[PDB]
Length: 258
Ligand SMILES: Cc1cc(Nc2nc(/C=C/c3ccccc3)nc3cc(N4CCN(C)CC4)ccc23)n[nH]1
View 1 (cartoon, rainbow, N blue to C red):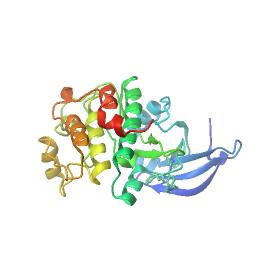
View 2 (spheres, protein in one colour):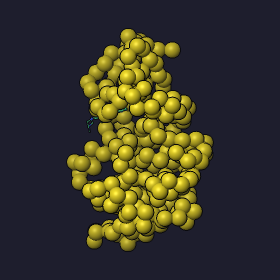
View 3 (cartoon, helix red, strand yellow):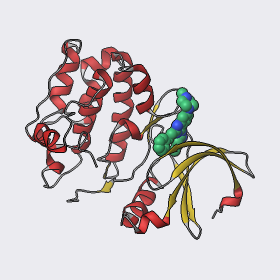
View 4 (cartoon, helix red, strand yellow):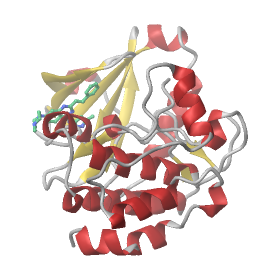
């Protein structure tokens, strides 16, 4: 059981809607950590109150070297706070902004780790759904780490921008564990190209592109990368491979890092 007067707040790390997240230190232990505070005001004013309590509990016991740890939570009058693992090399989103694109060795590595992190998430019937670069942080070794289980869900269910969502969920419909493999294909595409495969500039253009799986590869995406991506980006879920198989796909193996 915790309170705010047990940590001292460092610099702000980033501000989204709901609340900000700061670097922080546990006053007793001198432990370095992240402190995402979420505003109980905007929580009642967005109805995600049941989604967060779900977010907390689910990650509150997922433990994996490529999943950000949630150590605990607490609330006061105006707000609630999550006390999170601190990942010292920032977001995958920002290193993509600064590099424009990644090379094969680098993306193959990210996909590997994310596959493993996902494979584990699956082994406890947890589907993430929202796997964009903005939820991927990097730890001390530049290893990828799945943050923000804001919209994760336990078991198959029927529950922003759609660039990362699969055809299943977009057109209503029921979805399973295979949604994250769509996401993984979308991610591997954005890692290599600099934009997700279905970027457009109005929501329904993008909806149509996803709906009919419409994407092209620029010339510099290799024979091996094109295969993998086309493999995961399948309208039909069950036609998408298993995380075991993608981990073993020769372009990943030839280019990943052990
Ligand atoms: C929860 C958590 C965050 C976190 N680490 C970091 N988060 C955010 C920014 C996060 C963010 C949050 C909301 C909105 C926008 C950004 N920015 C960061 C920037 C960092 N640096 C130092 C390393 N540099 C390469 C980039 C600037 C390092 C860690 C960061 N560890 N654990």
